[PDB]
Image (spheres, rainbow, N blue to C red):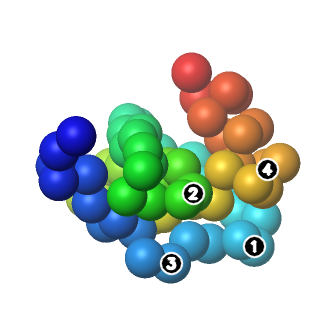
Amino acid sequence: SAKELRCQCIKTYSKPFHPKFIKELRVIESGPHCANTEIIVKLSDGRELCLDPKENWVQRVVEKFL
């Protein structure tokens, strides 16, 4: 019902990687505009990494950190 939705993370990292520099993480709702849910993490160095929810290790990152 709104065009507020946007696919910020065009590409995601599928290769397993668990950085200890993650302090915060944001979750973006895909909705009708985006077929896949977008998960992004924020590193203490001001770095952003896009993760694919289809990957099991990605869930581990979210679950373990939160």
Q: Secondary structure at mark 4?
A: helix
Q: Secondary structure at mark 3?
A: loop
Q: Quadrant of the C terminus?
A: top right
Mark 4 residue type: Trp
Name the front one of labels 3 and 1.
3
Name the front one of labels 3 and 4.
3
Mark 1 residue type: Lys
**Residue hosting label 1:** 15
User: Where does the image place residue 62, in percent across and percent down from the top left?
Assistant: 61, 34
Closer to the N terminus: mark 3 or mark 2?
3
Q: Disc number at residue 36? A: 2
User: Where does the image place residue 42, in percent across and percent down from the top left?
Assistant: 36, 50
Name the front one of labels 4 and 2.
2
Mark 3 residue type: Lys
User: Where does the image place residue 3, in percent across and percent down from the top left?
Assistant: 17, 53
Measure the alpha-carbon separation of dots 3 and 1.
12 Å
**Residue hosting label 3:** 11
